[PDB]
Amino acid sequence: AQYEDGKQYTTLEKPVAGAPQVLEFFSFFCPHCYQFEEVLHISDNVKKKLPEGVKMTKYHVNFMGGDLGKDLTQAWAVAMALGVEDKVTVPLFEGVQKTQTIRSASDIRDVFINAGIKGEEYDAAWNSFVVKSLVAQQEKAAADVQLRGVPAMFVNGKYQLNPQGMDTSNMDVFVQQYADTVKYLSEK
């Protein structure tokens, strides 16, 4: 067929009940993730192909960058809790990978401050139990699918995108194939 299990996607042999419809994993330390977000704009082009009523979820992972990596999973929980993902994603990626000015939890905090989140609001969230459970959700979702690398995308807890089975010559064309495949899997 045009879309074949084992080529544009793989099926999980151990399906995950109750999983978010479209679930993306990344790390701010992850070089292809930087590309996905800053150059390819994958999340955004996928969103534009999703049928109505399918929600999109994005989680950070702990397994890159050690201690700072974990701080970033907690910061991403804060980002989600405050609804400020679209204001901190670019400066966090650039702070970790471009300028390398993010080396501590305080430097992460500075990014939010500069993005206009009040210090007091940031600190309150950072320490909140709602953020703790949001950290727990990110960790559980990754655990559920035996997640060992990023970027990664899963559809309905049963299909995993396989971008390596795709032409990267043209970046536009790669992105739309990626997005079209998520739509296909969504309708499965």
Image (cartoon, helix red, strand yellow):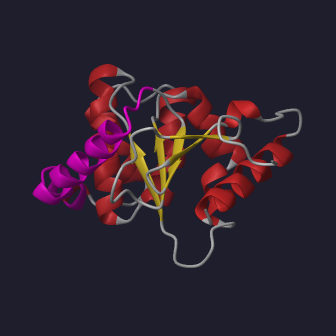
Q: Determine which quarter of the picture holds residue 109.
A: top left
Q: Position of residue 70 (x, y in %)?
A: 28, 32
Q: Residue at x 45, y 38 (%)?
A: 13
| Residue 100 is a magenta residue | no
Residue reaching furthest to the right: 169
Q: Is residue 121 left or right of residue 73?
A: left
For the question of whether residue 99 can be seen, the reply is: no
Q: Mainly helix, strand or loop, the magenta region?
A: helix
Residue 8 position by quadrant? top right
Please say whether residue 73 is visible from this viewpoint: yes
Q: Relative to 6, is 57 above or below?
A: below
Nearer to the camera, 24 or 116: 24
Residue at x 32% of width, y 31% of height: 62
Q: Is residue 122 magenta?
A: yes
Residue span colored magenta: 121-148
Residue 150 drawn above or below residue 139: above
Q: Position of residue 49 (x, y in %)?
A: 69, 66
Q: Residue at x 48, y 68 (%)?
A: 55
Residue 50 position (above or below residue 20): below
Residue 59, percent from left and from top: 40, 47
User: x, y percentage for residue 93?
Assistant: 52, 38
